[PDB]
Amino acid sequence: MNLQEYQSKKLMSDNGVKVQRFFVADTANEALEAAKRLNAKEIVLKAQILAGGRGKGVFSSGLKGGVHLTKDPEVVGQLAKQMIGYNLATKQTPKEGVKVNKVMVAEALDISRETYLAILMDRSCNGPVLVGSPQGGVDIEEVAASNPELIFKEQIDIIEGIKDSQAQRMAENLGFLGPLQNQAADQIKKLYNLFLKIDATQVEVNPFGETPEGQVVCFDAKINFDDNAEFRQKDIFAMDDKSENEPIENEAAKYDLKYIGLDGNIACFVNGAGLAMATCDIIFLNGGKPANFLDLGGGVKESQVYQAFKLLTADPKVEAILVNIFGGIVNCAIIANGITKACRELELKVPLVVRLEGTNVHEAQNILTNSGLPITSAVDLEDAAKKAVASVT
Amino acid sequence: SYTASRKHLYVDKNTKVICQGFTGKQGTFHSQQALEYGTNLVGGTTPGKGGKTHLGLPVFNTVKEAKEQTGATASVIYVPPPFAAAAINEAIDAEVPLVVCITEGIPQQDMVRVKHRLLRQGKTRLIGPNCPGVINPGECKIGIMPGHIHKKGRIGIVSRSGTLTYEAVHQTTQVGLGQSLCVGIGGDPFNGTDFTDCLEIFLNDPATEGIILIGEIGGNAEENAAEFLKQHNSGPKSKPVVSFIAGLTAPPGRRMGHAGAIIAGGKGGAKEKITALQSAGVVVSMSPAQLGTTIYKEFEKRKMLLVHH
Ligand SMILES: CCNC(=O)CCNC(=O)[C@H](O)C(C)(C)COP(=O)(O)OP(=O)(O)OC[C@H]1O[C@@H](n2cnc3c(N)ncnc32)[C@H](O)[C@@H]1OP(=O)(O)O
Ligand SMILES: [Mg+2]
Ligand SMILES: [Mg+2]
């Protein structure tokens, strides 16, 4: 899921993490009042979209730039009038841009030190890990490549919790000094407790830094969430902003379907994550471009099969569909039922290649046969991939 | 050490199994299939339903009572995500030797906490979660894999993917090699058994003459397995290892179905895994369809398919 900047910063602020003071506005007048309420020396007005490149974007009003600084609250209101209700286009959006319904009105803070700090569960050590670098303001991948010696880690014991000495050592290695080091250590603890409270897979602060006036601040941050914890994070997941997702991914989400759009024309319909990845892989190896990844899940039900198939057939990028099922917990007949019923209710305009193995394969194959649908049966994975690639221009 | 429990992975005809979540939809169905396969399924647990029978077998309120009353040495978990970590912990506390967790969807943080307890004991071995289970063909099946595609034989299989396990099984049965023991370690990032745990068992099992290792993007388990094989599978007795790593075409920063299958912060790509395994002497199949033929050819070159006349 995805949160707007104002949503993640509120979540952090509500948990003791220091961020810039801000308000969110959905009208130009609200932006004006928020700017007055801030009582700040300088104010930043920021359109709320998820895509990057806001600073050099252009609104459908004609206004250039999605991020503006001013000392004058009335200018905040005036510029907000040229943002709200309009589409913001950037290098990272489609040509049409994204509709801006909200702006953030925040205190503009100068940055005197920039560092990197992330918290995640370590994939090599059991338990949380703090990952930090004094080299802030760049992708962590760049630092790892150019200056691996500037990446520091503190392994945390999940039962003991974060210790003062761990937070202090990381703050020191990030380069904070004296009272700012004590501030940063305290903020690391707040970030750690937040990370556990919200079932994040990662809290990434970059830049984690300080102002010239002597305060440690999380200037910007990205939080990723564990989808497996949605059942105990309902309020956070209700904030999910889906307006910038592929619309097919949004439809798939409504039916709890794990769909990921790709740049290709051969749709994939598979009952396991490993086999789904391998199906994309083997399509590529035989000269094709998969249109999507889809893992129906071991607990897939017929209704989800039906919905998944309709999403594929309705996608204009799809020129053929490869169904590849090796059922264990998944009964192949559920696949055959969902597909045949989905096609009873529309014409099959693309070639359909089907590979079924495992649980109840013979009944499933008879269902496909007795439906009369035009199917190319495949004998194994390689044959399925070759026949799928052969079915497209 | 927790490594002392690795031996419990090797289920056999004398393993006795209880089902946690026994009265649920999947617990019921797969318990019925287990009985029909010949697995010694002796009962199960659902809290609050102790003192009932189900499939002609006793239902218990607790793992401790079930274990004491049946002599069970293994448990399989079909408990929904909100409670499955508690079910694992109950089985650890009861010192069940082998616990197999089928459930997909357990919060990652729950499993970090489970692993903390697991690593500080040596009585219980956990496979999973989010895994199809373990099978010794013709001897013991604990999980959801389709029974009919297996054949007792010569290849040990360990995989982060259930479906890809079935591919490797079907391929190795088709070419006549069969399987000694198949272990699905599951697709979650934090789990009870890794590749190295199974490789230890395979390398020391006389019945396992070759190994298929199936991985995917995410984490570092494949790299750890490569390091293990560098130290422990060199020499004249080295066993052939064949592998496929899924996800060379996966995009970065996205969980590909499995909670553990993501290239995150530049870490977890398939290319580096293939390189690490190749450096450890593993023969990596270009195609997921050719696992069986690839290991067959490795056997052939080593004169391991000669007929005794
Ligand atoms: C191969 C990868 N794995 C997969 O693809 C599996 C995907 N599916 C899942 O993970 C599913 O959540 C599961 C198969 C685990 C469960 O689904 P299922 O449809 O069987 O759930 P149900 O709700 O019918 O059954 C769960 C049972 O566990 C019981 N249960 C709950 N907590 C516990 C516990 N701590 N110990 C034992 N049983 C428990 C529930 O009471 C319920 O039984 P009941 O309905 O008789 O009261
Ligand atoms: Mg799966
Ligand atoms: Mg990044």
Image: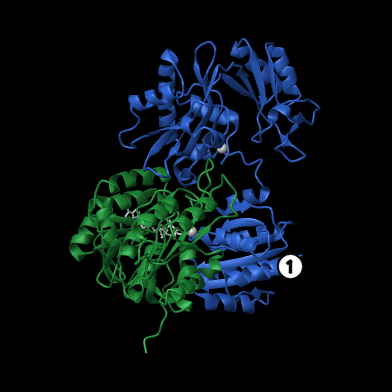
Q: Quadrant of ligand 3?
A: top right
| Tag 1: amino acid | Glu
Q: Viewer-proximal residue, A328 or B175?
A: B175
Question: Is residue B21 among what the camera can see?
Answer: no
Mark 1 lies on a secondary structure that is loop
Image chain in blue: A
Q: Give the quadrant of residue A87.
A: top right
Question: Is residue A44 among what the camera can see?
Answer: yes
Image coords of residue B191 (percent x, y): 38, 51
| Disc 1 C-beta below 8 A from ligand 2 | no
Image coords of residue A143 (percent x, y): 54, 33
Residue under label 1, please give it: A347
Q: Give the quadrant of residue A82.
A: top right
A117 lies left or right of A257: left
- The structure residue drawn at horizontal position 73% and vertical position 36%, both measured from the top left corner, is A91
Image chain in green: B
The image shows residue A6, relative to residue A40, as above or below, that is below
For disc 1, the chain is A
